[PDB]
Image: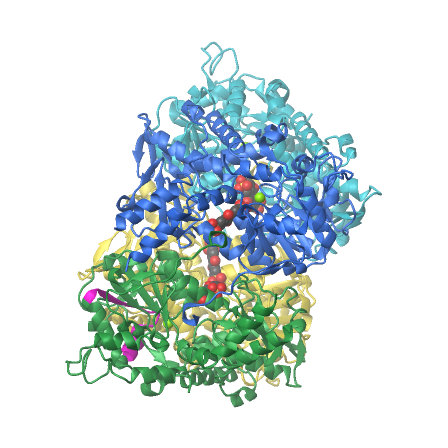
Chain colours: A cyan, B yellow, C blue, D green
Amino acid sequence: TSWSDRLQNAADMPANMDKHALKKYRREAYHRVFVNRSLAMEKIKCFGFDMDYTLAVYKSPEYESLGFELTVERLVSIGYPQELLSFAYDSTFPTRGLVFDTLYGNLLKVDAYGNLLVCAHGFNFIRGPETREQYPNKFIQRDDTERFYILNTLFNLPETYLLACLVDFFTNCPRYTSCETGFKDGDLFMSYRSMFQDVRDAVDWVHYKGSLKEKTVENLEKYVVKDGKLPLLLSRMKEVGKVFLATNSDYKYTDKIMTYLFDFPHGPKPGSSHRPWQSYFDLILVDARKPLFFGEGTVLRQVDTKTGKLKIGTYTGPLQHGIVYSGGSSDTICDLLGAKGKDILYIGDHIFGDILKSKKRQGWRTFLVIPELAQELHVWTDKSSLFEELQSLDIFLAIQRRIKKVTHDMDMCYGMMGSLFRSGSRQTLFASQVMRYADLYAASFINLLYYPFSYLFRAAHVLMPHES
Amino acid sequence: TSWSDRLQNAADMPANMDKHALKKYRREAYHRVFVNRSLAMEKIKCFGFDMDYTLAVYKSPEYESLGFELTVERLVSIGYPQELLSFAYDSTFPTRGLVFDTLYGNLLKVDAYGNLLVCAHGFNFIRGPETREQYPNKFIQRDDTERFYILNTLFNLPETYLLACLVDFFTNCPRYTSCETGFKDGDLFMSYRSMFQDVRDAVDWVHYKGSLKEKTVENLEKYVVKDGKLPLLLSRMKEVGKVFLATNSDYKYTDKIMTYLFDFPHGPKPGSSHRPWQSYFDLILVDARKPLFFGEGTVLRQVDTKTGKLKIGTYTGPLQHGIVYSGGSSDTICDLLGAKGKDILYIGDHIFGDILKSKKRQGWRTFLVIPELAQELHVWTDKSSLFEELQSLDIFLAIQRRIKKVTHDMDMCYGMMGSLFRSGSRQTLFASQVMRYADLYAASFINLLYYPFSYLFRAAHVLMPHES
Amino acid sequence: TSWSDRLQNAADMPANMDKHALKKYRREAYHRVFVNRSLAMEKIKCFGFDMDYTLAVYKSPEYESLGFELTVERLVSIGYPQELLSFAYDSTFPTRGLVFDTLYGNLLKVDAYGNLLVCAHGFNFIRGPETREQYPNKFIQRDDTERFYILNTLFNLPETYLLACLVDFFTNCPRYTSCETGFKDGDLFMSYRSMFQDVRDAVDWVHYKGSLKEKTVENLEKYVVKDGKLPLLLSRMKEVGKVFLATNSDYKYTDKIMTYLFDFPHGPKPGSSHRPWQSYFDLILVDARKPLFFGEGTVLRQVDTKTGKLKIGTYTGPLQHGIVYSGGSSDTICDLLGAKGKDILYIGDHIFGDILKSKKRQGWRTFLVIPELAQELHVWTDKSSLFEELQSLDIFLAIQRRIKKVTHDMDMCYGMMGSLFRSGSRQTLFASQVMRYADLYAASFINLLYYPFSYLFRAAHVLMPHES
Amino acid sequence: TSWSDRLQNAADMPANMDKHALKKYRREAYHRVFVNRSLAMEKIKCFGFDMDYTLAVYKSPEYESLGFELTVERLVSIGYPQELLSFAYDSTFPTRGLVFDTLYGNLLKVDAYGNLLVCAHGFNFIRGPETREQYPNKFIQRDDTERFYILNTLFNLPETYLLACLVDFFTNCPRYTSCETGFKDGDLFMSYRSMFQDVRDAVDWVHYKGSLKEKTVENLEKYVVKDGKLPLLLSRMKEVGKVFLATNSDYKYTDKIMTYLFDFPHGPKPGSSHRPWQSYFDLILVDARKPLFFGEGTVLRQVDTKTGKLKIGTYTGPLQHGIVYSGGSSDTICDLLGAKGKDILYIGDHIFGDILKSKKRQGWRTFLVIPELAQELHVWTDKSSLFEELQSLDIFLAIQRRIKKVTHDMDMCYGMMGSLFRSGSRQTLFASQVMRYADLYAASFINLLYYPFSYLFRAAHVLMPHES
Ligand SMILES: O=C1c2ccc(S(=O)(=O)O)cc2C(=O)c2ccc(S(=O)(=O)O)cc21
Ligand SMILES: O=C1c2ccc(S(=O)(=O)O)cc2C(=O)c2ccc(S(=O)(=O)O)cc21
Ligand SMILES: O=C1c2ccc(S(=O)(=O)O)cc2C(=O)c2ccc(S(=O)(=O)O)cc21
Ligand SMILES: O=C1c2ccc(S(=O)(=O)O)cc2C(=O)c2ccc(S(=O)(=O)O)cc21
Ligand SMILES: [Mg+2]
Ligand SMILES: [Mg+2]
Ligand SMILES: [Mg+2]
Ligand SMILES: [Mg+2]
């Protein structure tokens, strides 16, 4: 009973649209929208969406195994050793947002300042003192993107596990010899860095040229959460403003997935005519290339919706009923929807390209979807007085072992790599970017349905130490 | 009665080093050290210092007029119109940390997300609606450093006022014609951008080639706060660890200033032999070139202390009693003092080059000195129930004019450009970087003297919305 | 009767290895090696080869049609209009080395200084005065590689013709409207630049992912010149030094092509055992990535010759009998063959990546293969007294129309875009790079067979004006 | 009897403007204009000039000692050892155009392909075999500008000698220890690279901030060649076209120098009113910043000619009688003089910034002034049958020691570093750029006076090997 089970449970009940019962629904935390900076929904004019892991939520672990298997295969297919084929995806290992150190082949879970919180090498969890040999100040320069990778998104889950599998594998294959920075095999030396590259290449490959999409769209129920309430909310959004899709995915794939998400024997609400997915949007934009989308963008194109091929040249015309865009930029959406940024709420799951960049570069309002938040919330309250015990032991410091021990037992409930948002008392870089960049966040955007359209989402004013 | 008056008042009383009276001293807020992230002083091994506006605090407005006058002069000297000479520095105008928009020649005071809080053009304070013509989403892309300048440090005070003077001047000189982006004068067009460049050039000029230093060191009492307690604290620091100076200033100037700061008829405490300033440091480094200092650095050199000229070539020897370094990097200091970063507390006033970069790039502990914090703290409590009234009006929103009105009356107490750390209920980008990068901060580092050496500076653990 | 006909004619006669008959063979110009800077063959220790259009010479126009057809198809396949399919490759149009101006969609044939010699738009040959509207100083900045493309190699022949086809097509399709910089079609605007990109993408596509290789290797006799003398020369080279292959092509393709080039019922000379192509080389290197190969290179890999896949990691071992390399750099070849540069003769057809860069970056000796030189040499002597007449009319200038007229009649004999090496009296950029970078050059490297191994290739010493 | 003696000899005779006597004057080689590519003077519309070492030719060795002395002094002044003061400039050492290798501290004289022709370390002339330890292929990558410097211009003469002085000095001072790449002195290591930087800094310093200009303009007759014929030629140029000055020098200095060049008790010809230097130009542009001038340029400014200070802002007006420009670009000159490039003849002495870049980037016609060409031409004919003997010994190679010997005796006549344009039979990189970029060249532009205005300067058409 993972987190996509929770979402497909929530998904399976029709909304009681009675006002009283909505207020009580969104009392339970799995259904709350959480506020980081106040936001007056009255003033949002356009709602805009990402697709993958936002509107279309890939069932777990099923989808991650598929990615993993396909990547394992690709790699064996280009000459990595047969033993990889015997690997099998373990959803209890990877937590999202870890940084992969390509110098020493460690997975690292870090705070906002790049302080080490957990360091794993293969599957050996390197303890405090022993990490000082490689990180003498228990810290990593987060900005050194040549060395540190950071696996931010749920697509990175398979690779997160895979990297740990490969490191452990070679550490323990007597054919290879460990070195500080990689493995020797006679006359061939494979550094963790180039190893890591190979994994990245292979994951891209299964996405853009291999069989992930193809295997996905032929078993949508296996891999993709479907929720009656989705058409309802979008329809409700379009009643008070403008609704738009801007997604990195291409049109053809976007079409297969969205069709499915709307495939119900009715429209927004039981008993109404089914209308096609496109009718739910005032502007549809694909091949977005976020985060570049939030800067110079790319040349604006028109999609020929029959073929699914792009028309030839640069689209210079206006927003017409039926048109579909490819590329362009976030200004395209602004000009065309006659919106300036704080007018818009952009809803997506990518902490960097969907959230951080639209806020920083454009002044857009932000809603971050976090799937795991479903499971993480069961664990947070199931185990609440374990945490409250940790809060107590820190406060009594006015014995250190019992801290590090309790912390461990806590993190363990979450997975081998702990909560998404913290390691014991200390918050992760990911938690830290949620609070800082995501104005609102939830386990799923569908949680918006439970708030009235005029709702005022309200966060407490921050005070500086010297102001208290 | 400004803020350097407060510091020279505090400076003028000898420390009562009785333990009880120290605890009570640092109760009053002007003397508190404020904590943003917990820090156990027991574990700091090296204390390191900036000089300008840290150890040597330039008396205000005297020092700022001097800078301003010298810059005004330089500019008239390269052909700017005589009328500039009649300008005169106004300490009630500029607040530090404003961003100068070189496209439209506005001073802008912004929050962490680059939202407009105050916008001034020349001296005309552009109100809400009218700012939308130029900033249609009431926001600026903070990362667009080609366009936006940001005047971060107390050295920037003179230029902050100067830029407003120049814009207002030309707006109203009938010889020139206003344009969106600058001024026409017959066949010459001077954009705000190139205007701004000229000001920057001229300020650098008076610092590196003009008479600022020379006029300063010949009237140190006029321009530089001197405090008996300084030698005392450094001496106390050296008793429990290592003490180091790493400053952007060159040696000669560093020597004149530091000599003065130690010029008392005694040592660390009344009745003891006066020892020279260098004896207070285990490592002295000049020509630091921060923030580059916190990256690749520059080639490490040795200062010939007789001449004050650099020796020829790259210093490869060890830390020797008496040696003075030039350039190098922050690793130089780490290797040589046998320190890893969290061991160190670096104390300085530059929010970017001293604080943000040492934390981000090196994992160094940080103490930010903020002079204005002295005055800003009188105003914060003198006017406390005005603010508490603002907190009330926001909360009653569950009438808008009364918000914007009260906000105004509040900010006005601070200056024309308001508090350093906020504009009414909303925090500035500067406030936001203090909390995020500066582990400790105070009106002056001397506030450290009032805490025991084993003190545990303690900040409350952050919780995410969904965790509460 | 083109130029690959000439080579397959020369190819089809066995070498008379009698010394007297060799001296007389290489008297006729099609068989000469031409010298630009003296070179003592006695001192060359390693001969090194490119493959495509060097050792393996693609029959013309057959190969070019194939490329063209495949590219035309690709483009229609991504949405370019059906009419392209009716195009058909015209070998009498393109001359190699033209520059494509992506601003205005012209093919330009230029001298070393980028002076215009011929300018064609679609198929309209823009005359003198009319070119001044777009090139007011009859010149182009050759270094402006963002704007100017330059189609240098015989692979570029199909695209050279294709670009002219497309420009002419749209100029004259009433569905589109000409503009200075591209074509409007309702709301879509396709600039020549982006048009040009599409063509480039499509040519790469048929090479790396489409069916060019696949269609080629299944009809080698159709597409690839085979010459008994090739194994003979290589064998003769290996008798006096070291022989190496360093090619951009991957191993699999390199294997199919080279096998074929050596597919004869005998070895180097009629009656001897056939030996496999690899035995002819002391070092075999593929995936060369020239010209980067002549700088930092890429990571050195080993080819697993059974699979044709790369082994995993970086090859650190020595040169072993049987080994095949991938990537690396030109230093790899130097270290491993124990050669410094002037020791080596590198033989290839790419004026930039094979010749200019190895000379400039490494001090390697150079032999440039130029296929067209076969046909161009028939034309040069067939029409010799036309040229000698042009030389006369220039000299009598001490009437202008007769110059421009004779020039035309001359260039026409070569093709629509004239000789490779000149336009009337004036030399091309290509000619100019041959003389400057290619130490020796010939219609084919096989011309080396006709010179003794100790031969001294001898060019006249240059004198400066003031020295004569 | 150097080369500036020759020019001041030529300078001192008034021109016999009789047509017959002009034709005979320009028969003698010191007075010839040499042609690299034909040029019809009938078609030049604007003549444009550099100043330093073009119109104003600094007397040698006097000027070079001054530069050298001033640089030596600067360096001792920043801490280089006293012994430098005892150095003294030796005009028989440096030849222009040498490359300084900052890795190993060698002066290198190279051909166009960067082949070594002479290599000196300090003053030790490293012979053939011994150079192979450091340059194993007797070659340098010319494009590696991080390592190789190249001292191109007559201003570089002092530094050329200075670098050799310093290297020799430290090689032989027992206080220092030689290393491959620099010198150790206890704990200080000074690499040749950083040494070289120091020299460069110091030369810039004496030019922009030290006393070179100031000492120069107070003894113009000592340092600057003055020639009656100069006003005559410019006046003659202005009669048939447009005349312009575009110089890197600032206005004030440009004014002192040009005033002097025109300081005669008459105008263009004895007996006419003296007119001021500015009247000789249709466009005057200073602070040119060549070669950037030949690209994006800089912002166009107007000079206030009373003060010599720049007016404030960007000049947008038209070409007005009396106006003086600062910065801008080469398009400024083109637009304003209504010229496209081949219309213009630009006359200057900088092989890169004056000649190579205007030709390559703009299609401008070029005249290169080469002062040394005066002396080099005495030596070329004084010693003609020594060279003709070298030509003979090369040809008889169909004994090697006698080549290298004769070469030596030849080069020696020129200086320690040989002719500017060759080392024995082999041409320098400098010679090679003259022929390739400089359409015309002469010992001085005054040689133009001896050609009629309609003259056709005529170079022989180049033929490729295979065309002969
Ligand atoms: O450059 C980044 C990037 C840089 C730094 C971080 S972070 O330190 O975790 O905030 C995070 C990121 C990213 O998450 C990311 C995602 C996608 C791209 S893309 O290739 O331009 O599309 C670039 C990036
Ligand atoms: O590049 C910056 C800089 C960039 C961005 C900001 S900030 O947005 O206010 O944090 C702030 C800054 C700075 O405060 C600053 C201070 C000194 C230099 S220097 O010329 O490299 O020494 C660069 C900088
Ligand atoms: O950058 C160039 C290039 C630049 C300039 C010229 S040229 O002006 O004709 O000499 C010619 C060229 C080339 O011919 C060429 C061929 C292949 C590459 S690659 O993409 O790096 O492999 C780059 C280049
Ligand atoms: O970048 C160069 C440069 C590069 C290469 C050569 S060359 O190899 O001798 O042709 C020569 C040169 C130069 O002669 C030169 C002169 C002045 C400048 S400046 O600092 O931009 O003004 C740059 C340069
Ligand atoms: Mg997403
Ligand atoms: Mg400071
Ligand atoms: Mg080739
Ligand atoms: Mg010059």
Q: Is residue B313 toward the left or the right of residue B29 in the image? A: right
In the rendered image of this protein, does residue D350 appear above or below residue C259?
below
**In which quadrant will I find the N terminus of chain D?**
bottom left
Relative image position of residue C456 (x, y in whole percent): 61, 60
Depicted D228 relative to depicted C306: above or below: below
**Magenta stretch?**
D240-258
Can the viewer see residue C403? yes
Give left or right: position of C431 versus A169: left
Across and down, in percent, residue C133 comes to: 27, 46
User: Of all residues shown, which one is farthest toward the front?
Assistant: C20
Task: Say left or right for B405 vs C25.
Answer: left
Q: Does A311 sit above or below residue D336?
A: above
Q: Is residue B468 visible in this depiction of the protein?
A: no
Most foreground residue, A88 or C336: C336
Q: Please identify the quarter of the rendering in which residue A123 is found.
A: top right
Comparing B351 with A142, the one in front is A142
* In the image, residue D319 above or below residue B135: below
Q: Residue at x 51, y 23 (%)?
A: A252
Q: Give how far across and how far down residue A412 sits, in percent.
A: 73, 38
